Length: 96
Ligand SMILES: [Zn+2]
Image: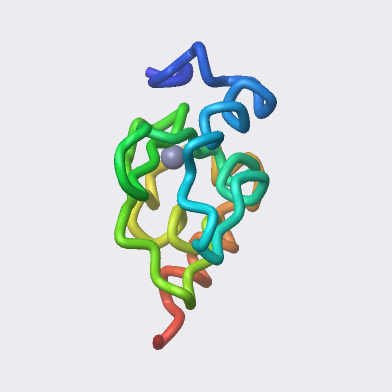
């Protein structure tokens, strides 16, 4: 059924605040990861989505939150409602 997997982190602001210990040297800044529906696990570079509860880590230089989101967590209703199913389909088709 649909409702946030982490209702407490439904609001962006609440999600942002968890990145205070986020590894500064990373390309993915907190505001980015936050907007893409992610909150910080407090450990390493691991984050989880408030809606799908999916967690992504090992963030490489070439990674964009939304895209990574769409790629691995394709069934996430937050992405579909923000980016739309086309974006998802597109990201799912992209070569690299
Ligand atoms: Zn998600």
